[PDB]
Length: 53
Length: 53
View 1 (tube, rainbow over the protein chains, first blue to last red):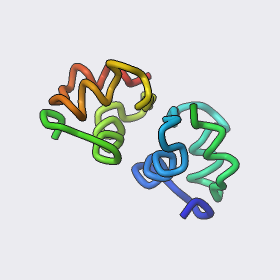
View 2: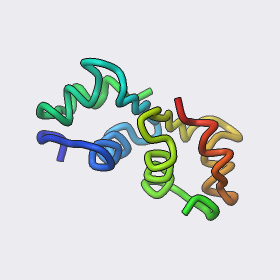
View 3: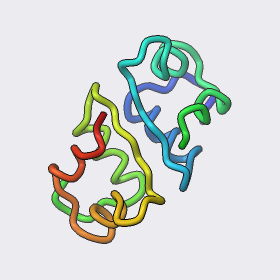
View 4: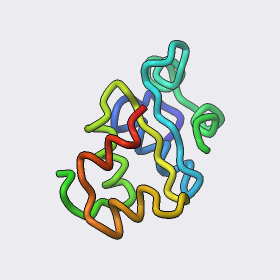
């Protein structure tokens, strides 16, 4: 589920599932941020975990 | 949608919708944190916005 383009609620769901009890931060308005890496390009587990707490 | 018990993905979805382009942080393992206020007790828009960036 993480190796695809994930945007909007689809991205937030992936963060929720990957990060679990660590939680996460979703900051879509950071340039070259999670949207650039996971929505407009193909996401990855490595990049999602960058946003877990 | 925000004035009810919201847990797990249901809570993350509410944060996503409320916070919009501000983004948010989801930290379930903080005591008296968002889980205590929104999942085990009834959530509110006021409390959700506490977690927007």
